């Protein structure tokens, strides 16, 4: 009780710095149909290819970054098989690369933060990929040269919503421990889900057109040091809820051939139509009355999803413009994406001369969604911009 | 403003463990006759000098009993499961995705029944397993089978090894402490379907995991600010921390491949664990000014007989201190992250039956210990609670 009051922080969790990274291989969406069909030896599937081209154009993605190259596909051709065993080839890659790519985003965040690594007390790290013991948390802590006493937590194989969920965890770690400085990191590399095309599974090609790679990192803490730590946002509330009877709406299976993902065509409608209950619970206490009263850091998912959310909530096009930019310029980087959107929102706020880091509004929602259906709402307070 | 609201949101006291339930699969595997069954069913009867090496292993493990989801009939339906290093992942995944959540349901139901409050009052779920990876997760499946509210904040932690049972306490501590009214369902479930396989002579390590490892689940409910007269704390979480021993990633670990999980270890793993406890125990027990290691009680993840022996021998603990770890490891084997919950359950049960003054065998402070790959040391400090008889 007396111990309890002393060992705990006083104020809200704060996002103090944001870093992002991608692999160095640019893949342009306009020539991706050509690369994909040539290197998976599928040039005799011209009708499927032409269909692939149309799908690519409609994804509205311009570029993605992938760790995978033609070199890697020639050296381990089982990565190309659509349903033969290829798990070992995939594991060899992700167990190594998931921590390396994470490091890039972590370093950049830690640099903006401007404090000694020795002052990090916790690391919370998520990825779909790179399962091994010890795990990717261990490897990442080690690459960065974190102190050995750092509390590490790895969250494997949760999908797109995990980015937001990490904020939910970081909130409690930062707030309940005086002095805690949490390194939060999302990294995804599509090597476990990449595969050649199948003429009887045209829809599943949506994951070959839509997913890219990337890592996002932040430093979260309560009680910012005056004149040394400048908060970008305050986490005011963070929560999750599950949509009844929507397990079949989106998800996947980890099998001998790697990850396969599935979705229903109505997934945009399903997400859009079930957001209102969540956001109500999160924002009514603040007395906001219009969805356009708050700023939005949305995980895109895909263009249809952004669309259906924009239509259902009646959002002016500025609200999700940041989700759209990031998605068009990088694709869906699963759990990482929302950090890119975050980063893009606070930079634009500064460049466009806005009063806050949330585009001039006080309150925001950071939104993640994934298999469940799972909705992660994280309520942000913006911080003043002094131009 | 948000300093104001901050005060309204947060809890007041320490996180407390409020209930503990445990469960196993229905299938009894006696260790005296396990070599028989394990050679019969893996079609390895036409080998005989290995058969005697293994009976000798099973004898030295000190395990009497384990419970496995696996049966002979399942191995008949899915022969690849008995293969040494052939691809078997699909079969293994078919079972774990389905069964991990079902076994965790049982432990959780038990905890919730001891607790005796409605499921609607559960606000978080933290759930770990080596196994059962699907999207949505095992966490989603358990939530649904239990009928938890849709608004429950879930967290699944896959594929961390044995120390994860203790690490969850470290997380639930912060969830319970930072939220007024938070009630956190903490569950651990392990089923060795992914690791079970037949023998190879050029491999001793694998052989140990066919002998030492068992199935089971544990569940506790964690909350701060207990409702007076309704919630009865068994322990208070005072502190929880993690430490990694330098240059020891090779001491114990594992790999997830198309043949399932493979686990390695160095023979000196007992020495390694015991020689590196002092640092953790200092940062943990010095604030309380503890004189002798024998002054606190111990809820230690057993791991194996040698490990228990190394710890007792290094900290000069009297036999009573780890006798609960020994009992669980003897009657259940090593259930990875779940084991420590069976150990906690044992200590508090005996404490009651034997007439003790507290839930920690009569003592005030105690340490709960997890270890696994890293090397990772999980240290949770427990304050026991009075036993009114």
Image (spheres, coloured by chain):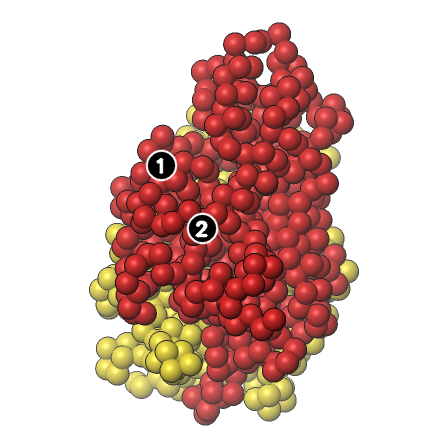
Chain colours: A yellow, B red
Residue at position x 27%, y 79% in the image: A225
Residue at position x 65%, y 38% in the image: B67
Neighbourhood count class around disc 1 (C-alpha, 10 Å): few under 14, some 14–19, many 20 upward: some
- Report whether A260 appears left or right of A191: right
- x, y percentage for residue B126? 57, 60
Secondary structure at numbered mark 2? helix
The quadrant in which the C terminus of chain A is found is bottom left
> Is disc 2 on the same chain as disc 1?
yes
- Report whether A204 appears left or right of A162: right
* Relative height, residue B1 to residue A372 (above, below): below
Chain on which label 2 sits: B
* Mark 1 or mark 2, whichever is nearer to me: 2
* Relative height, residue A307 to residue A236 (above, below): above
**Any part of residue A39 in sight:** no
Q: Residue furthest top?
A: B46
Residue at position x 45%, y 62% in the image: B170
Would you identify the image quadrant in which residue A277 lies? bottom right
Front-most of residues B59 and B214: B59
Residue at image mark 1: B269
Front-most of residues B2 and B201: B201
The quadrant in which the N terminus of chain A is found is bottom left
Chain on which label 1 sits: B
Asked whether the residues under the numbered discs 1 and 2 touch, taking CB atoms below 8 Å apart as contact, a structural biologist would say no
Quote the CA–CA distance across marks 1 and 2: 23 Å
The disc, 1 or 2, on the residue closer to the chain's N-terminal end is 1
Secondary structure at numbered mark 1? helix
Residue at image mark 2: B320
Would you identify the image quadrant in which residue B350 lies? bottom right
- x, y percentage for residue A296? 53, 75
- x, y percentage for residue A101? 37, 48
């Amino acid at each position: 009780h007396a111990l309890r009051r002393e060992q705990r922080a006083q104020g809200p969790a704060t996002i103090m710095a944001i870093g992002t990274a991608t692999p160095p291989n640019l893949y342009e969406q306009s020539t991706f149909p050509d690369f994909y069909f040539r290197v998976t030896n599928s040039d005799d599937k011209q009708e499927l290819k032409k269909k692939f081209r149309r799908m690519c154009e409609k994804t509205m993605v311009k570029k993605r970054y992938l760790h995978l190259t033609e070199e890697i596909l020639k050296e381990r051709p089982k990565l190309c098989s659509y349903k033969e065993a290829s798990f070992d080839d995939r594991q060899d890659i992700v167990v190594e690369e998931i921590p390396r790519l994470a490091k890039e985003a972590a370093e950049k965040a830690i640099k903006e933060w401007g404090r000694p690594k020795s002052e990090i007390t916790h690391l919370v790290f998520c990825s779909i990929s790179g399962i091994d013991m010890p795990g990717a948390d261990y490897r990442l802590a080690t690459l960065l040269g974190l102190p050995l006493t750092v509390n590490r937590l790895m969250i494997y194989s949760q999908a797109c919503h995990m980015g937001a969920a990490m904020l939910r965890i970081a909130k409690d770690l930062a707030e309940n421990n005086r002095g805690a400085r949490v390194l939060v990191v999302a990294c995804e590399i599509t090597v476990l889900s990449f595969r050649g095309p199948n003429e009887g599974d045209f829809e599943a090609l949506a994951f070959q057109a839509g997913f890219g790679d990337g890592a996002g990192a932040v430093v979260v803490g309560a009680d910012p040091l005056e004149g040394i730590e400048k908060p970008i946002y305050e986490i005011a509330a963070a929560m999750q809820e599950t949509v009844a009877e929507s397990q079949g709406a989106v998800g996947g299976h980890l099998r001998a051939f790697g990850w396969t993902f599935y979705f229903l065509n109505q997934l945009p409608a399903i997400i859009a139509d079930n957001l209102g209950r969540s956001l109500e619970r999160a924002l009514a206490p603040l007395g906001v009355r219009e969805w356009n009263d708050v700023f939005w850091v949305a995980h895109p998912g895909n263009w249809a999803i952004i669309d259906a959310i924009e239509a259902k909530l009646q959002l002016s096009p500025d609200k999700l413009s940041t989700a759209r930019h990031v998605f068009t310029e990088y694709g869906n980087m699963q759990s990482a994406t929302v950090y890119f959107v975050m980063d893009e929102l606070r930079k634009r706020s500064a460049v466009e001369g806005r009063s806050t880091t949330g585009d001039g509004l006080q309150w925001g929602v950071l939104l993640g969604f994934g298999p469940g259906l799972s909705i992660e709402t994280v309520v942000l307070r913006s911080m003043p911009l002094h131009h």
